[PDB]
Image (tube, helix red, strand yellow):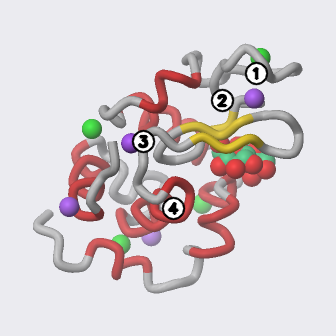
Amino acid sequence: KVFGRCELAAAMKRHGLDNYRGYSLGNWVCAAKFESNFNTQATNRNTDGSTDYGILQINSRWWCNDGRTPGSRNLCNIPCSALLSSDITASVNCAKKIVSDGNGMNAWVAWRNRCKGTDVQAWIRGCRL
Ligand SMILES: OC[C@H]1O[C@@](CO)(O[C@H]2O[C@H](CO)[C@@H](O)[C@H](O)[C@H]2O)[C@@H](O)[C@@H]1O
Ligand SMILES: [Cl-]
Ligand SMILES: [Cl-]
Ligand SMILES: [Cl-]
Ligand SMILES: [Cl-]
Ligand code: NA
Ligand code: NA
Ligand code: NA
Ligand code: NA
């Protein structure tokens, strides 16, 4: 599924992301934009051999199991393939674990480099929420 911007904002808010660990809804929408371009099916192999999956590009080294990442933890206890669904429930539950892990949203490279410090409220502008 390719989410619309406001569509994803509403799903994220419904799942309780708005101000989760103090991160406003705009931060999460911005992160999704630059991690996956709002595409639940997005996958990207990383240099260490792990792969990032789904709307928030959750990683196979720590968070989900894709059966091809040695040293793999699966801290969200979920197959990575389950993070590609049109239903973002699993991705959101896992993201909640990631952002609570110590470094907040800095865990997401694209958020740190492209969202952090910016006018993230723009990402929910015009949405009926
Ligand atoms: O996720 C924990 C830890 O892993 C790092 C390593 O670069 O980021 C990886 O995991 C993120 C969350 O799944 C991915 O978005 C990212 O692309 C992937 O490199 C750290 O940034 C993070 O603290
Ligand atoms: Cl915001
Ligand atoms: Cl693995
Ligand atoms: Cl959803
Ligand atoms: Cl924080
Ligand atoms: Na898609
Ligand atoms: Na939309
Ligand atoms: Na915030
Ligand atoms: Na992998």
Between the residue at mark 2 and the residue at mark 4, the CA separation in whole angstroms equals 17 Å
Vertical side of 48 occupied by 60: above or below? above
What secondary structure is marked by label 4?
Answer: helix
Q: How crowded is mark 1: few (under 14 residues within 10 Å), some or many (20 or more)?
A: some
The residue indicated by pointer 4 is 31
What percent of the width, then of the height, locates residue 28?
Answer: 44, 59
What percent of the width, then of the height, locates residue 43?
Answer: 60, 40
First-in-chain label (3 vs 1)? 3
In terms of image quadrants, where is residue 34? bottom right
Ligand 1 contact, mark 2 (Cβ < 8 Å): yes
The residue indicated by pointer 1 is 73
First-in-chain label (2 vs 3)? 3
Where residue 114 is drawn, which disc sits there? none
Residue drawn at point x = 51 percent, y = 61 percent: 31
Q: Answer yes or no: do the residues labelled 3 and 4 have beta carbons within 8 Å?
A: no
First-in-chain label (3 vs 4)? 4
- Quadrant in the picture for the C terminus: bottom left
Residue drawn at point x = 70 percent, y = 54 percent: 103
The residue indicated by pointer 3 is 40
Task: Give the amino acid at mark 3.
Answer: Thr
Q: Which of 24 and 54 is in front in this view?
A: 54
Task: Give the amino acid at mark 1.
Answer: Arg
Which quarter is ligand 3 in?
Answer: top right
Task: Give the amino acid at mark 4.
Answer: Ala
Q: Answer yes or no: do the residues labelled 2 and 1 have beta carbons within 8 Å?
A: yes
Which callout, 3 or 1, points to the residue nearer the camera?
3
Residue 102 visible in the shown view: no
What percent of the width, then of the height, locates residue 126?
Answer: 17, 78
